[PDB]
Length: 80
Image (cartoon, rainbow, N blue to C red; front, side, top):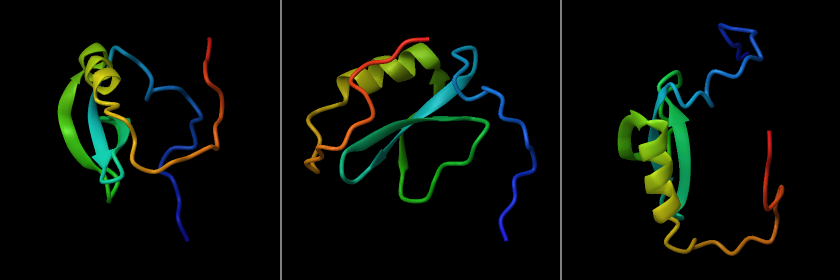
């Protein structure tokens, strides 16, 4: 079956100290992927590996109104 090479449940993917790339799926699905992971099939890199802030700045503008109409959510906000 499948298996990870690292059992660590650490937070390395949300370090703004790391450079991330901005991906998209044809349903105008935008996401932020870390260099510590390979680009998931189905998602194309719209913005290459850049400092987390540039990535977020781009994503924040590239909402451009989503295609699929969803009513399922996690939460409208978040803190930490």
